[PDB]
Amino acid sequence: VQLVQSGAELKKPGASVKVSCKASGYTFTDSYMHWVRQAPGQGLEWMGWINPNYGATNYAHKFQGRVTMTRDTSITTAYMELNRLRSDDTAVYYCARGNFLRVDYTWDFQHWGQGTLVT
Amino acid sequence: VQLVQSGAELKKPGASVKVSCKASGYTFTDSYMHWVRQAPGQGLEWMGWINPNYGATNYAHKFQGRVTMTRDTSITTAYMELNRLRSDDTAVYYCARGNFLRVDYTWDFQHWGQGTLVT
Amino acid sequence: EIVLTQSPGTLSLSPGEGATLSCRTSQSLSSSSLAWYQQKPGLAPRLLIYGASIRATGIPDRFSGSGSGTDFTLTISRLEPEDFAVYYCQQYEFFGAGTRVE
Amino acid sequence: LWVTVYYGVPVWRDAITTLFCASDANVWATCVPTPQEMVLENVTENFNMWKNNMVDQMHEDIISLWDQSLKPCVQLTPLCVTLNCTDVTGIKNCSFNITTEVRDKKKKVHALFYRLDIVPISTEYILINCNTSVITQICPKVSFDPIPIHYCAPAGYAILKCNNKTFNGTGPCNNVSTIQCTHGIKPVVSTQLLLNGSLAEEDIIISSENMMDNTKTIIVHFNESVGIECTRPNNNTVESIRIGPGQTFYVTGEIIGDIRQAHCNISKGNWSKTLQRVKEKLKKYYHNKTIKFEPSSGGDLEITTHSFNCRGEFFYCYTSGLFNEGTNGTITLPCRIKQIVNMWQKVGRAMYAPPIAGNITCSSNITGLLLTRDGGRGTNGTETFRPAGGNMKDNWRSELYKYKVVEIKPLGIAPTKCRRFLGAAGSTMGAVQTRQLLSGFVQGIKQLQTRVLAIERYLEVQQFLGLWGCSGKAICCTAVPWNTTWSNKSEQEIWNNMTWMQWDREVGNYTDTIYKLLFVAQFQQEINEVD
Amino acid sequence: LWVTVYYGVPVWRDAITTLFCASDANVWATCVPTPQEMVLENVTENFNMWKNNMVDQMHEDIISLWDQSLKPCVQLTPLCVTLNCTDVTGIKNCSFNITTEVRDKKKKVHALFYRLDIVPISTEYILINCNTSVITQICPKVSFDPIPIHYCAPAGYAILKCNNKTFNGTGPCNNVSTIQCTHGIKPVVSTQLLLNGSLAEEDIIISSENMMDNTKTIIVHFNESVGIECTRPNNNTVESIRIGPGQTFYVTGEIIGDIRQAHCNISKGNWSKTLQRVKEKLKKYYHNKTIKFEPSSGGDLEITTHSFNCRGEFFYCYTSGLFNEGTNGTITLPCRIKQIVNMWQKVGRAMYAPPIAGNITCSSNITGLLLTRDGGRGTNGTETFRPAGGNMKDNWRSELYKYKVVEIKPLGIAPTKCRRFLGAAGSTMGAVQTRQLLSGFVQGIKQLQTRVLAIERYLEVQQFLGLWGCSGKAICCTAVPWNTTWSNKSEQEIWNNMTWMQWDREVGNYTDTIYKLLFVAQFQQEINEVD
Ligand SMILES: *[C@@H]1O[C@H](CO)[C@@H](O[C@@H]2O[C@H](CO)[C@@H](O[C@@H]3O[C@H](CO[C@H]4O[C@H](CO)[C@@H](O)[C@H](O)[C@@H]4O)[C@@H](O)[C@H](O[C@H]4O[C@H](CO)[C@@H](O)[C@H](O)[C@@H]4O)[C@@H]3O)[C@H](O)[C@H]2NC(C)=O)[C@H](O)[C@H]1NC(C)=O
Ligand SMILES: *[C@@H]1O[C@H](CO)[C@@H](O[C@@H]2O[C@H](CO)[C@@H](O[C@@H]3O[C@H](CO[C@H]4O[C@H](CO)[C@@H](O)[C@H](O)[C@@H]4O)[C@@H](O)[C@H](O[C@H]4O[C@H](CO)[C@@H](O)[C@H](O)[C@@H]4O)[C@@H]3O)[C@H](O)[C@H]2NC(C)=O)[C@H](O)[C@H]1NC(C)=O
Ligand SMILES: *[C@@H]1O[C@H](CO)[C@@H](O[C@@H]2O[C@H](CO)[C@@H](O[C@@H]3O[C@H](CO)[C@@H](O)[C@H](O)[C@@H]3O)[C@H](O)[C@H]2NC(C)=O)[C@H](O)[C@H]1NC(C)=O
Ligand SMILES: *[C@@H]1O[C@H](CO)[C@@H](O[C@@H]2O[C@H](CO)[C@@H](O[C@@H]3O[C@H](CO)[C@@H](O)[C@H](O)[C@@H]3O)[C@H](O)[C@H]2NC(C)=O)[C@H](O)[C@H]1NC(C)=O
Ligand SMILES: *[C@@H]1O[C@H](CO)[C@@H](O[C@@H]2O[C@H](CO)[C@@H](O)[C@H](O)[C@H]2NC(C)=O)[C@H](O)[C@H]1NC(C)=O
Ligand SMILES: *[C@@H]1O[C@H](CO)[C@@H](O[C@@H]2O[C@H](CO)[C@@H](O)[C@H](O)[C@H]2NC(C)=O)[C@H](O)[C@H]1NC(C)=O
Ligand SMILES: *[C@@H]1O[C@H](CO)[C@@H](O[C@@H]2O[C@H](CO)[C@@H](O)[C@H](O)[C@H]2NC(C)=O)[C@H](O)[C@H]1NC(C)=O
Ligand SMILES: *[C@@H]1O[C@H](CO)[C@@H](O[C@@H]2O[C@H](CO)[C@@H](O)[C@H](O)[C@H]2NC(C)=O)[C@H](O)[C@H]1NC(C)=O
Ligand SMILES: *[C@@H]1O[C@H](CO)[C@@H](O[C@@H]2O[C@H](CO)[C@@H](O)[C@H](O)[C@H]2NC(C)=O)[C@H](O)[C@H]1NC(C)=O
Ligand SMILES: *[C@@H]1O[C@H](CO)[C@@H](O[C@@H]2O[C@H](CO)[C@@H](O)[C@H](O)[C@H]2NC(C)=O)[C@H](O)[C@H]1NC(C)=O
Ligand SMILES: *[C@@H]1O[C@H](CO)[C@@H](O[C@@H]2O[C@H](CO)[C@@H](O)[C@H](O)[C@H]2NC(C)=O)[C@H](O)[C@H]1NC(C)=O
Ligand SMILES: *[C@@H]1O[C@H](CO)[C@@H](O[C@@H]2O[C@H](CO)[C@@H](O)[C@H](O)[C@H]2NC(C)=O)[C@H](O)[C@H]1NC(C)=O
Ligand SMILES: *[C@@H]1O[C@H](CO)[C@@H](O)[C@H](O)[C@H]1NC(C)=O
Ligand SMILES: *[C@@H]1O[C@H](CO)[C@@H](O)[C@H](O)[C@H]1NC(C)=O
Ligand SMILES: *[C@@H]1O[C@H](CO)[C@@H](O)[C@H](O)[C@H]1NC(C)=O
Ligand SMILES: *[C@@H]1O[C@H](CO)[C@@H](O)[C@H](O)[C@H]1NC(C)=O
Ligand SMILES: *[C@@H]1O[C@H](CO)[C@@H](O)[C@H](O)[C@H]1NC(C)=O
Ligand SMILES: *[C@@H]1O[C@H](CO)[C@@H](O)[C@H](O)[C@H]1NC(C)=O
Ligand SMILES: *[C@@H]1O[C@H](CO)[C@@H](O)[C@H](O)[C@H]1NC(C)=O
Ligand SMILES: *[C@@H]1O[C@H](CO)[C@@H](O)[C@H](O)[C@H]1NC(C)=O
Ligand SMILES: *[C@@H]1O[C@H](CO)[C@@H](O)[C@H](O)[C@H]1NC(C)=O
Ligand SMILES: *[C@@H]1O[C@H](CO)[C@@H](O)[C@H](O)[C@H]1NC(C)=O
Ligand SMILES: *[C@@H]1O[C@H](CO)[C@@H](O)[C@H](O)[C@H]1NC(C)=O
Ligand SMILES: *[C@@H]1O[C@H](CO)[C@@H](O)[C@H](O)[C@H]1NC(C)=O
Ligand SMILES: *[C@@H]1O[C@H](CO)[C@@H](O)[C@H](O)[C@H]1NC(C)=O
Ligand SMILES: *[C@@H]1O[C@H](CO)[C@@H](O)[C@H](O)[C@H]1NC(C)=O
């Protein structure tokens, strides 16, 4: 499983970032593309998952209304766009493929990408 | 089984003949096209066979290096080209279809063409 | 809403020792609902046990775990130098704060 | 005691097998038309709506029939040409040229295409999903109506139906019934509201694999239908375009009158009453919190809107007016008509649904509701439920949740003194095999494979009985004594106050243990007879 | 003595039957994954590698799977256009125009084609075999790797394997073994050197139908593998060309760096040692003469060169450096890459093998060698052996020569006093039928036909037994006396020092002679009972 993420950059209040999680070498359609937020030296958080065959997405109650998660299946690249960033959005961002991808049906995030440390 | 051979002509030392054995009315691909040399008023000789689906050919030890047996399957016509003819090449030439064409697996040449008496 | 508290302490230990780690769940869930993660200093986290007893591929034998209901436990018998990093207990959606080993 | 072989035992095991559609006297009725039911007293079985196999077979059989039915139909590969499209609203008047029936002559034609059915490349457009899929026109004069489809089990198998009214989909059932053919299952197509389904008998039924897991759609069955009348009010005129030898391409053209919007009416009376009932019921299946509803998240117009199929016209009606917070009225929903649609997403295939002259109307009965739950540490004690779409098998889990497929297993080896359909399932062993159960083991390529397999299982049981000296008889006393290690129980314990099923569960470990003894004992008896 | 019917006899006859591939957990594994072996003491069978049927079934099953696997793939009929080709060597830079995804627009594209893949019509060319065949691009994202393929016999049949190490392919075998599924047979494609085959256990094995016949390929199996590492060193860049709705055409373009030649290395150490061993062994199987080797005769680059298939790239490596007359080194062979190839020559079909970016490497194990013999009255006492190609079945005769398919035949009628898998094949009649042999008679359309046929043979034997009064028993004493004309032998001669097979050969002439007597005797007994 190859996941190739993008690069980070500090975004001023009111801008918009578009981070990508370009996948390769597996059945992209039959694979969730959960997103995970790493607070700086702190516990993780669940941004949201995106079924890529239909785009059916569910975000967290914290970031509901501020984020949007597009997916592209032709080039098998999932997206995650975050608008209206504030300075308190300092974190790292990774994409995890799991939730019945592995043997267990429960959320078992195995492969992870490359990280993106947008502050 | 119709086999229509070509005409003969005396060839000087160093020339090249191209005799043909144009077939019709059967499965040309699944049929060997053995060639047979009749010495003048003498015993016959085995020039060589040619599987026409692949061109896989085997000539005799006597004429190995002096002869070449092309085949054409589109028009279902087999060929036999003889270079570097000498005056001692006086003979007749016929094409025989056999070697499991008939019931027996062993070489059982039945149908023969029209003859070609290149001297 | 599923609260995943973790035990305190920094575990000032040397290599060759053992380590006991624990995570609590706020509702009576089965063992399949909880997993454990290595949290490295600045690299991608990886999964050890999913289902609270089934190990993952490419993982040594020194890690084991068990638990049902509440008070799930992870035990490491031999702390190699690379094993002195943070460790997270993952629920369905809410990750854990992470107990510390020095 | 001594081993004893019983043939025609009323027991079963969970298994996966090929069924076959039946229907009633079209895509489906090209199935063989028929339904007996018999209640099973004192029987409890652990049903599972989610790990079922009839949904995974119904999905593939819908794919297979939709692929088979669209093989002798037009392919719009010549129609992938540049389209000069202007405004006629969401509709575009597109002019383009084609290779007509005489191949060395080109003809210019016109057609009204919706904006969702074309993408730009100015005013130049092309039909959507041409450069990824091969569009196939849905054949006129072959109706694609979802007629009711029964599922009849093959020989040697049976279907158990759960008759408990409050049965959510998982767990034990109070009393079950063995049937040959299931009820009429209309194979509807929907996204957020299940249409024309089966109503719950007495109470609203809510179901999920695990509610605390959020990636798993929550199904809600209404016990009261909600009327929903919907319509495309445009006065279309269909124009036929000949593109080849017998291939015709039907397009919209020259709408007459006002270009009105397709709308989908629901009544604000019965709705929000049913939704308040659903809210009350979802209060109990979680920790106490306020229960209230949000519109759908972002996504493909195929999942962000309640889609369906009315008379071959594909509607995409927004549901933001339903899941956003009370008296009589109407909840009129905007809808977008889409012709080129690719449902059950197959990479490289599409479907041009042809147009219809005049208007159409779409009266249906909402009998269900698909939901999902937002997660996060949102606090405040309110749970936000959004409608969820995609994963089409859910639409047939709502109709195949009472049913379960079971494999009938004879040779219920039990001990006795001697030596040498499913009506009595819950009955004790003390106080019929030949008359009722055994005759039911023999009474396209799929339904031929399942019948050859039925023949193999009948021969693989009859041969076993013949090799155990039981060629013509159903009950055999045998020469193998009953070991003390095979869960030794007294005759009183076994042949009284104990059903065949529990006994099957008792000595399931000793399969292929008594069998070898039976083979060698019969061979010893025969070789003694010959000597 | 009196007639006696035995059921489950360990005997067999040569027959032709449908087998089925199994493979192990792609073109082949779309087969059902699985292999028991049991040695047969005192059994000798006349094997025949040449008149076998598994080669004639393996050939047709390779044709069937290659046709089935290339049905949902691109067809390069639009690509048969004039090609403006210049020099880039054996490679040509060809520019041409195509009908793109928008049909009324034409796009000019470029592609690097080898000179063997184009023919002239100047600089104008066309793809080879366009005007005789319909080229079909081999699908990417579906690997055509030759995975090992087992062959499991159906119900009622068996496969005998010959375990004699020095077994050449024809004649008796010292000791055999009945198996369910054969070993992993990689279906490789080669011309002159058999690659990735099965090594001989102890000694080099040479085989022909008749060596004095010259139209018949001589197979030689190496007991020691010879390493052969081969490579295409060109740094290709693959360019995708869209020609339709979802149809993509992958071409080479813009090689980076030096245009190097594909070469195929063999080691001069192990080779010519193995060839000297082959020479020594071929001294004995003819009249004494010097044994020495010549290059291949004239013919299609498909037979004049050792062809194979490495990672989907088709190599054509000349072998003139191997068969032309000693120390360590390398025997580097020039190779020609061909994309449009038509193997197993089907009139009207071809195959465009797509290109691969980067380089590739081709490490394989030569385990075989195909030869032929020049004839004529050449005198001098030297025999000239050339490599021979074509007739693809030979490549699977080298892997299916130990195996033989046999039809199990019950009803071994023998005389006794009384009246009224294959483990014991070589055992005498004196001192098991039900436990071991009889249960093995029931345990796509091809593998469904062979199972229906298994059911018919089980019913056509069970009905015969039931009509001979043997419904539930395997051994029957019957009311037909044993005639003196049915090769009358004493009980001592028959039931001692004589196996079931020789007895089957003894009274094979009296089939449908004792049978009529058995029918009429059973009918007489029953009609006496009723009266
Ligand atoms: C949920 O369930 C409801 C109730 O079953 C469905 O609504 C019905 O859908 C059917 C099928 O589309 C509708 O039947 C169609 O009705 C049209 C009107 O028919 C009337 O008018 C004509 C004269 O114009 C009379 O002859 C006729 O008797 C009626 O009075 C017709 O246009 C249709 O005929 C076309 O299709 C048939 C195929 O059977 C062809 O033979 C014809 O040639 C023609 O092409 C057809 O009969 C029916 O009217 C709907 N009922 C209501 C009450 O609205 C819902 O569709 C369903 N929901 C979903 C999502 O599937
Ligand atoms: C006789 O037998 C030998 C030994 O089996 C065969 O040689 C092998 O052939 C296979 C099949 O072609 C080769 O496998 C291919 O190897 C390539 C290199 O893989 C290495 O590098 C990648 C990174 O680039 C690593 O991921 C990988 O682990 C390896 O270290 C790959 O290009 C190929 O992958 C492609 O095909 C697979 C299909 O399985 C796809 O899933 C991939 O996406 C990709 O398209 C492939 O794995 C193998 O390397 C060969 N072995 C050796 C030692 O050379 C001979 O081919 C055979 N002879 C004949 C005539 O058939
Ligand atoms: C659908 O209905 C079934 C019952 O038919 C529900 O099963 C119930 O599941 C819960 C846990 O999810 C059980 O609670 C706990 O069970 C254990 C024993 O397993 C017990 O030790 C605990 O004290 C606690 O009771 C519950 O017993 C079980 N059964 C019943 C009858 O309530 C299922 O949750 C329902 N689900 C949905 C989504 O509708
Ligand atoms: C492969 O091996 C078989 C034996 O397993 C070889 O068969 C042998 O064939 C030759 C004739 O081709 C036999 O020679 C003659 O046989 C007759 C009886 O048939 C006998 O009367 C003569 O005196 C003479 O021996 C030979 O007996 C026979 N068997 C053995 C054991 O040598 C076969 O030729 C081999 N072929 C190849 C191509 O490897
Ligand atoms: C099967 O029906 C029985 C009643 O006949 C259910 O048992 C009880 O039903 C009442 C009324 O709905 C509930 O209040 C009780 O909680 C039920 N008892 C238990 C132990 O759950 C039974 O639950 C039904 N089965 C299913 C799966 O719904
Ligand atoms: C569907 O179920 C609901 C909920 O049980 C039923 O609504 C009840 O109707 C009775 C009628 O006598 C009232 O007394 C209750 O107060 C109602 N409950 C609620 C929560 O409002 C409804 O009748 C059922 N529908 C059918 C057709 O059986
Ligand atoms: C839809 O438009 C068509 C256009 O032809 C209407 O059909 C016409 O109806 C009028 C009614 O006065 C007749 O006089 C014409 O002869 C009809 N023309 C044809 C060609 O049939 C049709 O009535 C319109 N439908 C609606 C519902 O308004
Ligand atoms: C929605 O369900 C209602 C019943 O709840 C259906 O109304 C019945 O329809 C049948 C059709 O055969 C009529 O015979 C009955 O008289 C109707 N009953 C009542 C009480 O009106 C209604 O047809 C359903 N809607 C659709 C579109 O099928
Ligand atoms: C089967 O193996 C036996 C030995 O177990 C072969 O019999 C002899 O084998 C030796 C050693 O190779 C040869 O020198 C003899 O010539 C063999 N005897 C005969 C009569 O041929 C036997 O040949 C083997 N069978 C085959 C087909 O190779
Ligand atoms: C393959 O067979 C050959 C020929 O029998 C074997 O070569 C012999 O090897 C032994 C090793 O002790 C030498 O004593 C012999 O002189 C060799 N024979 C010849 C003709 O050179 C070779 O060992 C076999 N290979 C394997 C792997 O068994
Ligand atoms: C084959 O050619 C490609 C042409 O792109 C080479 O890929 C380049 O490799 C260099 C190495 O210095 C990189 O700087 C470039 O960024 C690469 N380009 C691309 C587009 O990836 C490739 O390395 C060559 N292969 C070999 C074996 O020489
Ligand atoms: C050619 O055969 C040799 C053995 O004769 C193979 O070498 C072995 O390969 C296996 C692969 O599983 C390794 O595990 C072994 O260690 C190897 N043995 C030795 C002695 O090196 C070799 O791989 C074969 N070549 C190919 C291309 O398959
Ligand atoms: C071609 O298809 C892609 C998806 O594979 C799509 O995004 C693109 O818009 C299409 N091309 C044109 C010109 O519309
Ligand atoms: C057409 O096919 C024939 C064989 O049937 C071939 O010899 C010829 O070269 C082809 N035509 C052209 C123009 O290449
Ligand atoms: C579209 O049609 C109009 C008709 O007036 C014409 O003027 C215009 O050029 C056309 N557009 C294109 C892009 O050909
Ligand atoms: C279509 O073909 C006609 C042929 O008469 C030509 O006049 C017209 O410009 C073409 N236009 C388009 C938009 O394809
Ligand atoms: C048993 O099922 C029958 C089906 O006719 C139903 O009438 C009955 O109510 C069920 N039993 C119980 C206790 O609900
Ligand atoms: C729909 O069509 C019918 C058929 O003529 C007509 O009677 C009715 O008025 C039309 N109504 C609308 C709203 O389009
Ligand atoms: C169910 O059990 C009761 C216990 O009283 C018994 O009377 C009844 O006959 C049983 N059901 C059947 C179908 O035998
Ligand atoms: C029957 O019981 C005896 C007691 O000695 C035991 O040895 C034997 O294994 C048992 N047989 C089976 C088939 O379990
Ligand atoms: C091939 O392309 C070259 C590019 O310079 C062009 O000059 C030449 O005319 C072309 N050949 C043909 C036959 O069209
Ligand atoms: C191909 O089509 C283009 C269309 O622009 C034309 O310019 C070119 O001459 C054509 N050439 C060939 C070689 O087919
Ligand atoms: C008989 O076959 C077995 C297979 O295991 C083999 O080991 C043995 O050597 C064979 N017998 C002889 C005499 O070669
Ligand atoms: C083949 O490709 C690999 C991949 O980069 C490269 O490392 C190697 O040098 C190349 N060698 C040749 C001989 O082309
Ligand atoms: C083979 O024959 C020998 C002769 O001594 C006998 O002992 C042996 O049992 C026989 N094989 C079998 C399998 O019975
Ligand atoms: C049995 O033997 C007698 C001797 O007279 C002969 O006539 C008769 O044909 C024989 N029967 C068979 C079936 O061969």
Image (spheres, coloured by chain):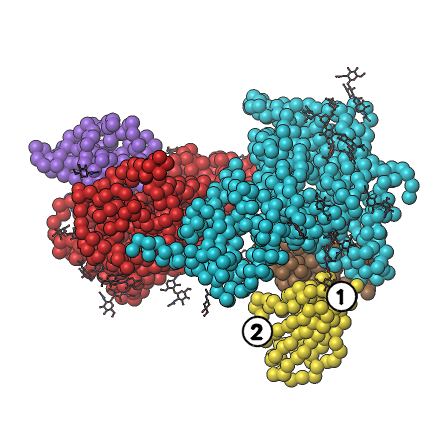
Chain colours: A brown, B purple, C yellow, D cyan, E red
Front residue of E416 and E319: E416
x, y (%) of residue D33? 60, 32
Q: Quadrant of residue B40?
A: top left
Given this view, does label 2 or label 1 mark the residue nearer the observer? 1
Q: Is residue C50 left or right of residue E120?
A: right
- Could you tell me residue D153's position as x and y percent? 58, 42
Label 1: which residue?
C27
The spot of residue D486 in percent (x, y) is 51, 64
Tell me: residue A110, above or below residue E489: below
Q: Is residue D479 left or right of residue B90?
A: right
Residue D378 position by quadrant: bottom right
Identified at 33% across, 37% down, the residue is E528
Foreground residue among D17 and E77: D17
* Chain of the residue under label 1: C
Q: Quadrant of the C terminus of chain E?
A: top left
Q: Tell me residue A79's x, y (percent).
A: 70, 54
Please say whether residue E5 is visible from this viewpoint: no
At 16% across and 53% down in the image, what residue appears?
Answer: E286
Which of the two residues, E67 or E102, is positioned nearer the viewer here? Answer: E67
Q: Amino acid at mark 1?
A: Gln
Q: Quadrant location of ligand 12?
A: bottom left
The residue labelled by disc 2 is: C61
Is residue D170 left or right of E214 when viewed as pictured? Answer: right
Residue sitting at the far front? E531
